[PDB]
Length: 541
Ligand SMILES: Nc1ncnc2c1ncn2[C@@H]1O[C@H](COP(=O)(O)OP(=O)(O)O)[C@@H](O)[C@H]1O
Ligand SMILES: [Zn+2]
Ligand SMILES: [Zn+2]
Picture (cartoon, rainbow, N blue to C red):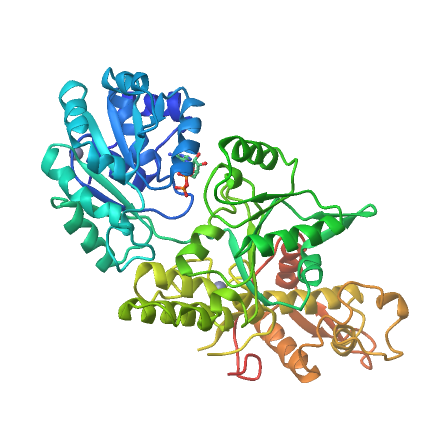
């Protein structure tokens, strides 16, 4: 067990990064790299705090940290974010002046961003910085690009194996997307890491509700369910990102949203630094409500309170999908992630990959598109399927407290609205709330029959038309009369209802108990649960 940080370390974190404490895995990596000078392979979920692991140590000791990445636009964005935290950083490339390079040699910058190509060609420069200043760490983001079995291989990374040779005292921190053992093996062997610490944060984002819908045929019909008509104009429910597979589909979606006068912006690769800066400005400040994006990184979609992610079209793969939905709910508030898809979507098109020569690669793409289509068509828990892919193992639904609840995914939410089996211990809270309310709404003056007719939307004359205006009228048609009758007998046995006759023995009423009235009081103001021992009559297999 590693030690807690000292006060000087915490003070540095507050002054430069505005955080009052390290996250657990952040400190795992930081202490290992900063104080133990040990190589690291770190797998961090979306929105955990990956960048702090390599930005903080060079700031704390006032030396240089080298960040190797192929995403030039992302390195530009992070440089700006660092300077706005009073941290000097720069992107080093062939196009840079010697004044920037001489300021680097004098130690004016804490964090230096380079591409893999520039790094392979200038190993002598790296050794000079190590002798004169000292390199705290070398970060290799997108480290899965080092070998084939990742979702995106690059050849420029293979020459990073000389870093350990030219700099055997400098620890390397490699960041990758999944906890895949095979990918981690390749990173260690190709980067020449020496017994590195292996850390994984887990991948669950419990505040992200997951849903998958089929496309309806036209864009406006697909998107209008996500809109609210305030006054006499349309609005998104909250800040929204719409991911499109192509620029063409981006323009089509934009053209349709403009029909409703929705405030929208686009986000693509190859945009200028000024364009990305302006999009970030408008999105963060809620001057645009929706960003329609074809990329999943950068300033433009770096926003804390994104409430809704929409994939318009099947996602490319599970890794892209996870990163793309990972942009939502970074403030901890409840967010929703919807995929709108059809079998003809371009990312599910097996027509356009017959012409790839590699044997294992073509089979990988076929299995990925089959895995994607299986997830989209699945009736089981969306969250369990996603967590299984990134843990490289079958995940149990009992591992996290979010699975199986109404805020988990659409397939879990369907089971709470109309239960089914796969001892039966199930949450009948939603159904009990309908029944116990109907008993109290009708005044506890009739038998259980009238509340049942109320819930099933009966046209009977026993029910006064004043009750047909109610919200619950007809919301129980999912269950038969005998089901509601049998469910009421379980509420009598458990002790939430009782049958009672007063002086008039020709009138039997069904009334709430003390426990019944107490439960309904809490359920009026909070979503309450009610666990039961059931029969296959209640939740059939
Ligand atoms: N130690 C910390 N305490 C609290 N919040 C943090 C900490 N480290 C990072 N964060 C926040 O987490 C958010 C996501 O971090 P970031 O590195 O941008 O995620 P990603 O690695 O997915 O891009 C950031 O807005 C950042 O402010
Ligand atoms: Zn230690
Ligand atoms: Zn679920």
